């Protein structure tokens, strides 16, 4: 299977012909040949986007909405193809990739729904005879740069909404998930969007991505990935004063208090901490439990972790966990386990690994110096920390450089609200999973987890600017020359 | 100042810089000594930052109405200090009585505006796509905010940033332009007398590349709001990335004033003189490139030059009717001389002006320019102004947009279709029909596009820059989860 | 034709069984048998909507949106049937019923798009430890009462938005357009909305309408019709403190200044004043022209009026004007012409009538005491008035009980804005027709023209309420007993 | 010496008719006051109509300046206002101090917000079309108020309606005319342009109905009894003017089994009996969970017993003052007698002397009791014991009213489920039923009225939206088709 770039309405090879073979994390079988594009390809996409910009931005919102409703209809027909690739390319289980595709349907529909309804403001003027209003205008060409864990839904949340308010897009997917990206471009092409409005360039982040980030004709970059990458991108973007949206790592706390249904809390914790092998930005990566239920919680949680079924995700619809995306991820998880053991952690269960598969390793007896307390653990290694009271719960929850999401389980309204208030995160959820996400809510973090919010109108805020415009209806006298 | 020394203001107290280092601030008007002021370093900036950080939670956590009360107290104090602010704006900044009067009136409105809005900054209650789910969005303050400002409108620019940032729960570390330190210290005087809690507002006087950079690179600083040169802005934005702090950047402008053929030409000339030369053209939103339709160009140019002839340049302390004061320093005079010399060298026609003496520089008006003139390619932060004659509205627009900047802009015309088409096509953050390019109100989104920066300031827009949205949910019913599937 | 009520999910005859025959305005021929329902039929519909309410109000908005998207799909299939009936029962020409059906599609889609995005507010509390927010709640059972001129679009605007946000509906169409009402019921039935959510009762206003207006379980009535009818409904509604939306008559001013393209201005005026025989709430009913262009304007206007083709609207697609809705309208226009001639008016053209057809009658030399200047002329009789300046234009424009829409033609920005500002109307359009309408803007008037606004989120404002809710997180001392 | 305030001038009514305002405390004469007729009201209405265009057309900042001036004068008049709220209205020091502090916040609030009421810029579905929505003031606004919180309620309607460019015709409750006069004094001293604000003192069915039926009045904002509200709404129809109606309430206070029972009793005493229970959002029906019901009733009655009833002028710690008039006492007596007769168990109180009524607390009541079926605008209170949360909600909702409501519980699930199911315009978890802030939407559903007041919600009531477009291209029209 050969995959291509999508530039100015045309599927085409990179200008060098350079290509790369992509393999499945599941068994190493070959999947496709994909472009290894370079700077010239990115520049061509940016140039196409730029030349398409004025026509795309200046048609009525309702027309852009019609293209998006069309893209929605095309997506609905391609659902099976997307699910297939999210599994074999990305390692996702059926339930995982099904969920991603449902959400992605909802995201495209949401962008379409909202395009006509993004409003500016009419202001009171402090001056006589003055009309004072504020228009919303699209930023221009927008770079879209994405990760590999939820490659479809993350890409589409950015792409659909950015397009909705009249920006054009240059899209560079994660090198482990280029085929998903190529399918998105297939969907867009079948939807018949004007040439240059959406462009796909497949290539290395440090080459194609950096060209996008540093190009003068790009107005904004919306980026999801590691904090370190985000910081580099932000620095590079400064040269042209382009704005950025950065959704970076998380190390979300899940806080379990002593008044919970302990069995339910364990079920919830298992799903939150380990869904998609814990490879989720808002995965519950640090579990924090009140000592009065800690023993029962830990037993029950481990009991349910043991029930998890790890297998070839292609095999059937009931597989719980698939493989990690590549061998480097397995190597890193081993470093995390090695660190925890060396610092006196107790390995209650798991740690076995074969190929790219990894059995969830669960630690207790951890302290704040463990790497799995200090770093984002983007994989199935999880600490459980026991605390004596709610002050400690909050202290532990905030003892991280990250600040994405978080959750508290309790039946007490005062403890729930106090903890929600006190925990330093961009998002918070009482009595639910840490990775709750809807299409039209402001999704994003604080501290090292990034800047900006995406989802519905918040995506619109990110890729538009306000424009104050006035009409003065009366002449007046001016202070200079005073001789007049 | 006859009874007090100029100092930093850190955690509730007026201190010396820790090195004791100082330097003499002199008047641009006559070189006379104004005061010794601090020359702080990274240590003093650090102490201010830590003070702001330690004050943060108590200041953010009180009810908004409490912060508004403090801003109302500040407003009352400002009204008492108005003459002192005007005096210093004139003698330290070189502004005329009418200029500094306007700045002080606007500053009063800015402080009041931030006080008015503090209680009313709202979040959102959302419809959940899920059953049994409450879904809402709170507004939270960003934290410690660095405020770094220029010398041209040092009071109103500083206070727009300071008053609004404080209103919504942030604490502040403020570093004024080195050419206007006494204005910053007077601001500190004002805050101190309003009795804000210690650490909530801090003033550090010292070099941008030292004190400023420390503010921009420090990890306990959440956001920087900055006004100044575009090159300085690019530098700050890149330094900002290291800690993922956000920035607000109000950078240069090269605003187009477009004059069409159906205008009252005399009114156009009067408007244009004011727009282009007020405060010696030292305004971010000064009308820096005048663009006139060929059908009225000859009479416009004659009229414009006629009124420019009347401009009275003098010592701004002399009386209330002085039109233009001096430029802020000698580097600026040297730079204007270059702009003038370049235009003449390139074949430009100097219609009037061109003399300078000390820090004083006369308006210098050119025609017969092309896009390669320095005064068409760069921001001319002084009284040197090109007039460009064009043949139609398309050329008006093409010329208007032929710039790296994109702050403001204006068109004069009585034709509704021409006005609206030109307003829509000009590439700027702000735009004004039948008014000056530097229109500004306390509560409107002020800011640019392209090289003129990012973000908006004024009223709720300032609040948008220095707060973040926080999505919170409550789920009222249990459910089953997909893993383990065996269950 | 098999026309019936639609109550609680079932098409059924009125309780008494009474029917009445609907004939065509075009030629008097039989069109269909329709119900003549009574109070019992209205009460049964109301009870059904009331019983259905909680289930409909409490599902997620996305679920209500789904039903509306389904309604949209059904409507798209019924287009030809709607155009047919609007022409044959309403007398609308092809181009008119086309426009109405195109706009109806947009109305339904608009209601669907917005359902999920109607937001409340999170407030700053002046108290410590207090959470303070505002929810949006549906008002409840909403009565929808509608007129004969744009029966489809006007009804669907009210019905679609009202349902979107969680109200249930009892709908009573105009007695002269009952088949359109029935076809609407068909669409909703086929869309599969839960029983009782939407209900159609075909009956006379003073019987079925008044029951709807006075019933205790109806929360709100949205009404469009004559100002006199509106005043009555508003008084009857007072008993049960139900709120109302009232879109009443208009007598909109079209103001033509001396700097215009006179030929264009004439073309615009003909369209705005006489489309659908001037039976439009926002018809340009009072034309006001500057003396410097009056003669040329009047000449050119009369010229294009004379070109208008009046005919059987069923014949072909290029018919300009069809019949008036009934004999009473013809009689009323004759009265209008009688009064005008009587007072010195100069009849420039038209006035001929046969059956329900009527040739547009255009008058000059009028003064403020003419009926055609004092009342809403819901038909093809139009005064042109000459004024000497802008002050006079505004004075004549505002010299009316009404205040719905209005328009000014000019290329001068100062004159356009000063006039826009000075004219007393709920709506105003610079360089366009008086009856400009979009699906998502606030549509409605001031003065005798009614109260409230409809369209998009403005319709939501009408049929929801704000609900302030707090949570206090700390205990405190109270002032009584003071001894405590 | 008390008079009307019409078009910048303090003047006697046309007919010269007056009447005597007496204190509810001891019947003492307070002042002679206008008894105005339809012509003093027509005069105020024409004054406001004629002042309107100048007032609405100045920039908002200038109206805000006038309100900040009003605030400065109000702060000077604080003591005067308290004194009159007490002697004329019957309020204790603590009640009137609260009302005055809140009123100050109300005037400041309207001033703060005047410059910031925004319209919208829209996306047009058409090409070459600018599409925006302006906010415009409705015009002359009638303000008609009740007697229980006459200052705060009046000023909430008046400050906000003024802020956004309406002019005002104000008729206060006949039982509290001096407070309305003091307001006119504050306004006169702030120097508002003549006719912008007008005070007419007189009878509701004369002065009030003229305001309500006058053609040049665009809006009436009303607070009072539901029946009066229905009458006003019907009359308003004839000129298609809009109305804001804040009517009675019968608010439920729901107390669940997991509470701090003592704290709940304290909160309940304050909520149910402050200002002698004469509050629209008073906790008028107390609903308590079986499991804590006995200890709650005991603790609640214990604290009610502690309430000090006395001349509110006597000192700052008096808990309760009198009812407003003799007729209120007689009504409460009917409420008490009906409950006794129906089998109710009177736990405490029920006595009355002069205009002072002793809080009467009942248990063992049913839904047929008058104090369960009607608004009890005084210190007579039923306690209903329930077995589960479903019963709590059923009892809470078994009323014609729907103003506010509250639940006390530490359980998040029960709190939210109950909050959602209670049919009320407002609701408070773990606080009193009558919580109120200056900038929040205050109002009810069902028989408690329509519309919301407070900050921008006040603005919404007394402004309309105006869609204005500019079309920048010409186009072809579909008639005549031959063209
Ligand atoms: C979130 O997301 C993270 C995981 O996703 P991830 O592994 O994809 O994060 P990542 O390494 O930061 O990469 C994210 C995206 O950025 C691209 N990228 C890498 N270097 C770049 C550069 N110098 N300029 C522009 N783009 C560049 C990547 O492309 P490549 O695939 O080519 O590296 C990828 O498309 C989690 O750790 C959590 O933090
Ligand atoms: C609320 O307020 C209620 C109690 O206060 P309240 O005794 O003052 O209620 P109220 O009797 O309804 O009176 C409210 C206001 O309306 C006036 N009014 C009475 N009839 C009127 C009419 N036909 N047209 C216009 N205005 C009229 C009253 O003036 P008068 O004082 O002259 O009657 C009074 O100022 C409680 O229900 C509480 O919940």
Image (spheres, coloured by chain):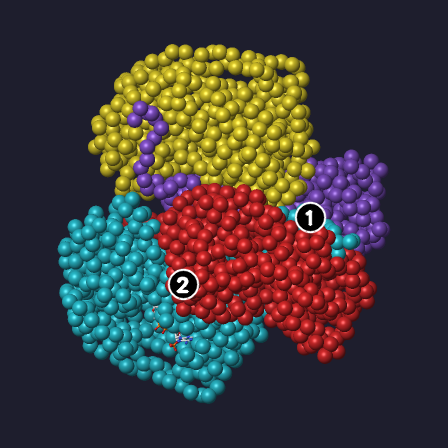
Chain colours: A yellow, B purple, C red, D cyan
Tell me residue D341's x, y (percent). 16, 71
Query: How many badges with numbers are in the image?
Result: 2
Work out whether A132 lies above or below B465. below
Residue drawn at (67%, 30%) of the image: A195
The residue pinned by badge 1 equals D128
Tell me residue A82's x, y (percent). 50, 25
- Would residue A342 appear left or right of D184 to someone viewing this image? left
Residue drawn at (30%, 70%) of the image: D91
> What chain does mark 1 sit on?
D
- Would residue D292 appear left or right of C464 to someone viewing this image? left
Work out whether C134 lies above or below D78. above
Q: Nearer the viewer, residue C481 or D13?
A: D13
Q: Nearer the viewer, residue A355 or C70?
A: C70
Front disc: 2 or 1: 2
Tell me residue C116's x, y (percent). 47, 44
- Same chain letter for marks 2 and 1: no
Q: Is residue B16 visible?
A: no
> What chain does mark 2 sit on?
C
Residue drawn at (36%, 28%) of the image: B482
Q: Residue D177, located in which quarter of the rendered image?
A: bottom left
Label 2 sits on a secondary structure element that is helix
The residue pinned by badge 2 equals C40
Callout 1: CB less than 8 Å from ligand 1: no
Q: Indicate the quadrant containing the N terminus of chain C: top left, top right, bottom left or bottom right.
A: bottom right
State the CA–CA distance, disc 2 to disc 1: 51 Å
Tell me residue A164's x, y (percent). 58, 38
């Amino acid at each position: 299977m050969k995959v291509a770039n999508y530039i100015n309405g045309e599927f085409k090879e990179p200008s060098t012909g350079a290509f790369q073979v992509k393999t499945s994390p599941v068994d190493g079988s070959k999947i496709a040949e994909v472009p290894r594009s370079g700077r010239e390809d990115a520049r061509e996409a940016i140039d196409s986007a730029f030349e398409a910009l004025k026509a795309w931005a200046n048609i009525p919102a309702i027309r852009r909405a019609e293209y998006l409703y069309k893209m929605l209809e095309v997506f609905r027909q391609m659902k099976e193809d997307f699910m297939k690739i999210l599994t074999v390319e990305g390692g996702g289980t059926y339930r995982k990739v099904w969920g991603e595709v449902v959400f992605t349907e909802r995201l495209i529909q949401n962008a379409a729904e909202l395009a006509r309804h993004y409003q500016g403001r009419v202001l009171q003027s402090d001056s006589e005879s003055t009309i004072s209003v504020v228009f919303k205008r699209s930023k221009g060409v927008v770079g879209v740069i994405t990760p590999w864990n939820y490659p479809l839904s993350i890409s589409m949340k950015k792409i659909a909404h950015t397009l909705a308010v009249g920006n054009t897009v240059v899209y560079k997917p994660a090198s482990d998930t280029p085929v998903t990206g190529w399918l998105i471009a297939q969907m867009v092409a079948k939807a018949g969007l004007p040439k240059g409005v959406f462009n796909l360039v497949i290539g290395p982040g440090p080459v194609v991505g950096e060209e996008i980030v540093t190009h003068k004709r790009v107005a904004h970059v919306t980026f999801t990935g590691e904090s370190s990458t985000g910081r580099e991108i932000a620095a590079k973007a400064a040269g042209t004063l382009k704005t950025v949206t950065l959704e970076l790592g998380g190390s979300d706390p899940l806080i379990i208090l002593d008044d919970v249904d302990v069995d339910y809390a364990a079920r919830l914790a298992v799903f939150a901490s380990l869904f998609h092998q814990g490879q989720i930005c808002t995965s519950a990566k640090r579990i924090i439990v009140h000592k009065a239920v800690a023993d029962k919680f830990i037993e029950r949680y481990v009991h349910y972790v043991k029930m998890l079924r790890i297998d070839d995700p292609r095999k059937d619809e009931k597989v719980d966990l698939g493989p990690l995306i590549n061998e480097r991820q397995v190597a890193l998880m081993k470093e995390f386990v090695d660190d925890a053991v060396s610092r006196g952690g107790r390995l209650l269960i798991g740690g076995r690994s074969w190929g790219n598969f990894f059995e969830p390793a669960i630690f207790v007896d951890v302290d704040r110096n463990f790497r799995i307390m200090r770093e984002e653990v983007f994989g199935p290694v999880r600490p459980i920390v026991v605390v004596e009271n709610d002050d400690q719960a909050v202290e532990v929850a905030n003892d991280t450089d990250y600040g994405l999401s978080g959750a508290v389980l309790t039946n007490n309204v005062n403890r729930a609200f106090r903890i929600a208030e006190a925990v330093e995160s961009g998002m918070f959820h009482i009595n639910d999973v840490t990775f709750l996400e809807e299409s039209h809510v402001p999704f994003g973090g604080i501290k090292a987890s990034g800047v900006g919010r995406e989802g519905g109108e918040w995506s619109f805020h990110e890729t538009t600017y306000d424009r104050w415009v006035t009409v003065t209806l009366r002449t007046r006298r001016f202070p200079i020359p005073s001789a007049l």
